[PDB]
Amino acid sequence: YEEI
Amino acid sequence: LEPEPWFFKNLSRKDAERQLLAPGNTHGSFLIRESESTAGSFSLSVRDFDQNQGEVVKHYKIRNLDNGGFYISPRITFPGLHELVRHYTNASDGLCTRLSRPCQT
Image 1 (tube, each protein chain N blue to C red):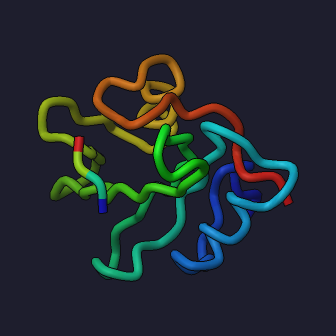
Image 2 (cartoon, rainbow over the protein chains, first blue to last red):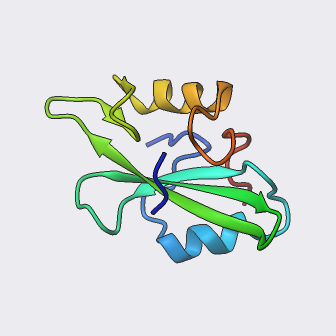
């Protein structure tokens, strides 16, 4: 997953 | 019942990638699906265009608040997924791209  | 155009309840991570990367979709195309990693929560999948990799799909965890609400970053929470989608359609606000159109099928 990407994060902000 | 009557899912929103962006809501793909039972679609897997890999099938989300497959469909978002298929013809008829483009930069910013997105969907929300049940998470395969965190039972009871949702995942956001969005197509992006990278200088290096070309077209790719990125996934974000949508966290649940106890007793209702959602967030991707604790900096800003929402009472519902409609508000979350509207927010990240209006501004990327930390995401890789703005949410543009729901996945076309």
